Image 1 (cartoon, rainbow, N blue to C red):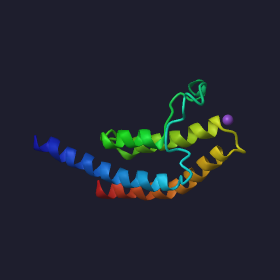
Image 2 (cartoon, rainbow, N blue to C red):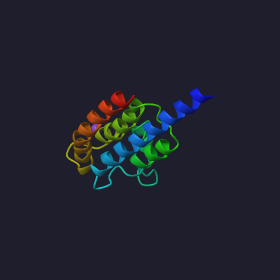
Image 3 (cartoon, rainbow, N blue to C red):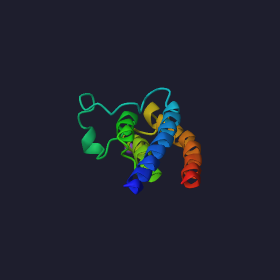
Image 4 (cartoon, helix red, strand yellow):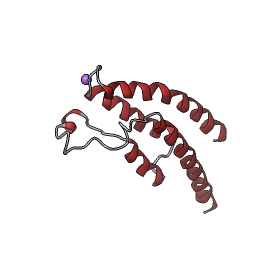
Length: 121
Ligand code: NA
């Protein structure tokens, strides 16, 4: 149908906007602490601690398969990155401190993206 295509055109535009958002969020991680999943070879007990791991590469695979239906789903995944890190790592570590910084710097990007998604529909 023509409806299904128009729907698909909007998913594709949401995907374009979220791609730009993802890039902007990932620039706030210049150390690449959150680039890739936590290694199970190097942290073998990780899944005893964290039940839903998340990272920027895994968000990128979902993004390019148009797997985010809305911004809420995308933000849930970004918060997992941050929240997992703040639980697994202690306060006085470079990892926890990197999460805090990504959260604070990410918030501004996310604020405007919500406006843009609401505004453009
Ligand atoms: Na902790």
